[PDB]
Length: 106
Image 1: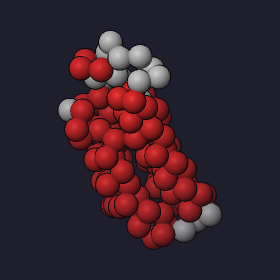
Image 2 (image 1 turned 60 degrees about the vertical axis):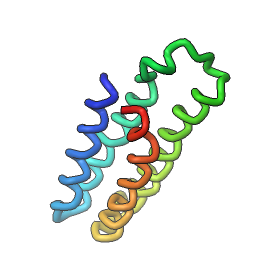
Image 3 (image 1 turned 180 degrees about the vertical axis):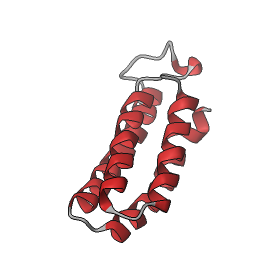
Image 4 (image 1 turned 90 degrees about the horizontal axis):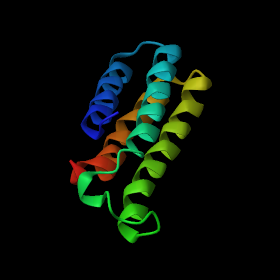
């Protein structure tokens, strides 16, 4: 899907997590965040379309989503252990990683 769409999918699931009461709700929203991050990693922006995959511009674009996914996975470990409030605090920190991976390419 689009980059702006995956950005919206991440923002929608972050709100679900903030309002969640149990860990299964957080785990489901984080699961969809991980898929949207790996999907946005494929949505090379038009300004970078002709760059080689080995270019530093494509390293930066790709690895921003690697970093987001890494911490989504860490949040998923907290949700799988039933730590709702801790997983919600980790999800709140995902906002900064989301911005670092997407914002300057919109």
